[PDB]
Length: 47
Length: 48
Image 1 (cartoon, rainbow over the protein chains, first blue to last red):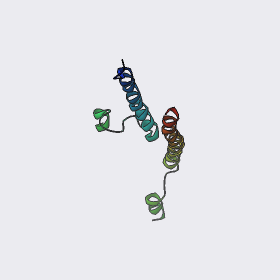
Image 2: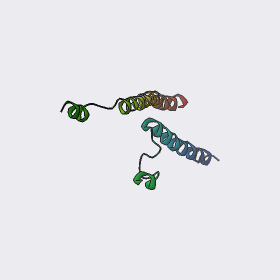
Image 3: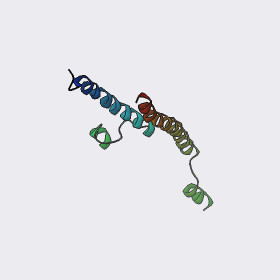
Image 4: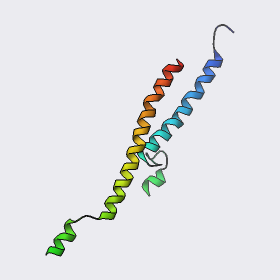
């Protein structure tokens, strides 16, 4: 009811995650590489 | 000696052309990407 906007709190969840995907894609394109830090693929990084 | 110096010194047309091509692709990408990156906070404010 009046006090708390639980709905908006739920919406907030959706922007960041998608934005993290956005940034991953952006940085991937800029670098020209799929694997830009060992986080994404340690094995591929080493190989 | 001329042949030896040439081999030590000259560069490989093919390798260097390939590198140039790759770098040009990267430049195009990065330019476009920076444009969009600036655009993104812009739409954040717009939706504000």
